[PDB]
Each structure stands twice: as C-alpha cells, then as structure tokens.
Length: 291
Ligand SMILES: *[C@@H]1O[C@H](CO)[C@@H](O)[C@H](O)[C@H]1NC(C)=O
Ligand SMILES: *[C@@H]1O[C@@H](C)[C@@H](O)[C@@H](O)[C@@H]1O
Image: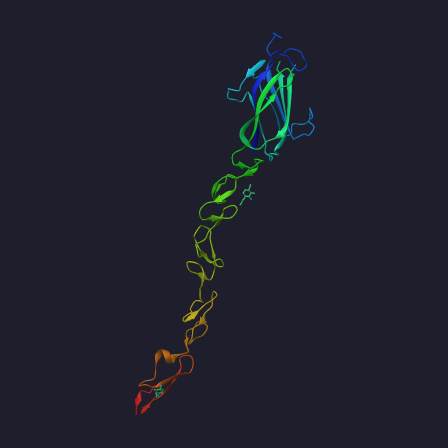
C-alpha cells in the first residue's frame, strides 16, 4: 500500500568524536551507521516512545566523513519503512548517527512535519552540533494505490468482475459497452425495452417471458390466436368481426363469404351465420333460384 523512504546524503565528523565527547582524534576512524524511528506527529517530541510507523538501521556506511550526494543510493545507505495504513500526512521522524564496535551515538536528529505521496525527495539537514549529516525523505504509493493516503486501490480489469481502466485519481473508467461503479453492467441495444429487455453482454437485448422483438417491446399473443391482438403476454383480444377466446369465430360471414346471389342483401346472425333478402323474381336461402 505505501512506503516512507529515507536516504543518507552525507556525514561530516571532522573531529571523529561521539555525542558524549569521546573518540570512536587520529586513533581510529568512526564506524558510522544510521538508526531511524518513524511515529505519529508529536506537538512536543519525546526521545523514547514506540516507533509506530516503522524502525530501521543501516549497516556501516562510511568513516568519519562521507559524501554520497553524487552516488546512487542502494540497500546499504537507505531505509525503507513500508505501511498498510492510510498515510496520515503528518509524522515525527527520529534519525540518529551511531558508531559500531559498546555502540554509542555520534549525533541525533528529529523532524516533525507533513508529507504527501510523491517520488520527489525532501532534503533535510543536521547543522547544529559537532557532527553534521544530511539525508532525504519521501512517501511513495505501491502499485495500484492512489490518493493522499496511498489507500485507494485500482487495478484495470476485463473479466467477470469488471471491464475498466484506471483514472489518474484511481477511479474506474468503463470499457465501451459497460457501465456501473464496478463497470460490470452491460449496456443494452439502443432501443431495448427498459421494462422487458435485459443484458449480460453489451448490445444483446434478451426478452422477458412473454415478450419478443429486436427491442423486447412486442407481446407474444396467446398460442392459437388468429385475427386477434395483445397489449400484454398471452392475450388474444379480437379485431372487428372476430370472436372467441382464440378469435377464430367469424362474426361477419357476410362481408367475408358473400353468400347471396344475383344482387341480394345479406345480413349477419353470429358465428358463421347469415340471412339473404332476395330481389325481383328470386328465391332460396342464397337467392339462387330464378323466379
Ligand atoms: C473520483 O475520485 C474522487 C477522489 O478519489 C472521488 O471522491 C470520487 O467519488 C470519484 N468518482 C467516482 C465516480 O468514483
Ligand atoms: C338489398 O336488398 C336486395 C333485395 C337488393 O334490392 C339490393 O340492391 C339491396 O341493397
């Protein structure tokens, strides 16, 4: 989730002394190493206290005086303090220069401040006292982590869980045809019924039971429906001159069949039924008999 990094830049111990006053002076060279303690911001800085955000120490870097400003900074001259919590922005940093081979302090430093995730280094100096030392600090985010606390996670996906890439703010930007916060809801065919149509995959309008068409907006009439319509699934509402549950009964056998012959007037009597009114010199149920 994140790392606080500390790099040693330089040490200047001209006299090759210690914090007490003793020598590690042409007797011997100081075996200079660094101890680091990182905790919560303190308005009134304590010497002790637990190192809540991390503790660490370097192996022997150099002698009495060394300059690493033009050098790279490797596993030996730097300390990495990782963190899984949200970066609180504010911190209290304790950096100490120590001599190896009983161990005793050379110079002690403390710094209370505020820092945001950034690859850019912040140089800090210990100018007071006999021994002078420089160092640089920074807080960087781990891969897929965003925000001021290096706590916002975003990894691009094109699978079961989502189809998106990540913003500069670690916000999900949906792939074409996807929507929602997790970018896992497919965008249906343009015109697809909001009531009876649904997705699974982009531009694929799947019909609700009893609905049909390219847009799932047309009801399926009751099976066996002839001369009837529907507004709802399984309906079979008859058109003019049609009757019955399935709209199969002809209520206008007259306008259909035209049974009366030689210009006679036809009248209805219900399901497939008629009546003929015959002209001059005509007889029969269908006015077929002349005279
Ligand atoms: C975009 O990122 C900002 C900052 O993290 C957040 O407050 C906002 O809710 C995000 N927008 C969306 C749509 O997720
Ligand atoms: C209906 O009745 C028959 C007898 C004819 O006169 C037709 O012209 C009429 O429309």
